Amino acid sequence: MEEGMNVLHDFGIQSTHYLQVNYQDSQDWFILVSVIADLRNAFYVLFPIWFHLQEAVGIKLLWVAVIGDWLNLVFKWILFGQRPYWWVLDTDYYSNTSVPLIKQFPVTCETGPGSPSGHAMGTAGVYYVMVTSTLSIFQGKIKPTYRFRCLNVILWLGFWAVQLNVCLSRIYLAAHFPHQVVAGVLSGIAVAETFSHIHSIYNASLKKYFLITFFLFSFAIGFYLLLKGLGVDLLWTLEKAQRWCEQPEWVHIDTTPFASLLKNLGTLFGLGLALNSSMYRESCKGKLSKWLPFRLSSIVASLVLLHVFDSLKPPSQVELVFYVLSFCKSAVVPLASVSVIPYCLAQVLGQP
Image (cartoon, rainbow, N blue to C red; front, top):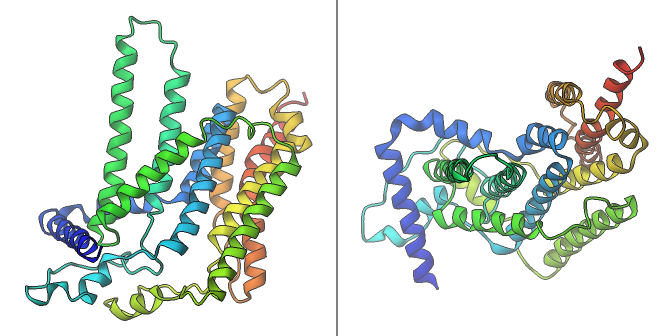
């Protein structure tokens, strides 16, 4: 197995070197792509638009993103991934030859296992959901089926172009291997396909949401403690990251390994509370639900206000307070977009 892993890592390093040497003018573009591919966008800008255009698509998108990130976290704990930017200077594979020369950028020194990829998984799942939803909705073109085939081709080409750019962004930056992004894309597609045959989540009571959140929380923490007690190292990437980085300022130490989990659970619980609240059942499901200007105004407000609100950062001096504040902060975005803004808009322009 060692020979295969070494060959795969060598192929990844060679690809990174080729991309960095021959495409030195795409640095800003690749950095911008890596910044755009974050999941914060999928929770802040992508969700409100699709939710207010088609509620089922938005709910499916949020569920897919949350479950994909949860699986990513658990398998990141298990799989013991690797990264290129310390493997190039760490391994003894290049003892007999010349070590390849690669460049490190201010966004390449990172802490944590290198598998599976997170950006690739999130983008693959969310964009597959969006493309499939759009193709299903627009299956009523009054044309001799030529225009629909053209739309299929164009949309699939766009999806694959986005996937290719995201895959190349993490390879040029020397932060992933090709197999670690291929597997992430395949896993995201698999999850997005699996949540196409689950019809028990579009109308679920608050008890079900609470039980699912509690089960996920309990399983995550129990698995963490079981791994800790079984003599398994869980802090090994930090040493390599702080040792092999070029400068001792790009590396960011967090010492809070329960941030993404709590943020995802908070978003899920906020959606659960919003869906069963009285504000949602009164405003978003009343008379002003089929009128396009109301939905457009809701989208615009839920974008601007959420982007302004995102500037608030919880303190990180106390771990428990940080966790509670992060949970409550992530639980507001769905609870805001679904419930509060539509209610305020309906009250403002519904009392003549």
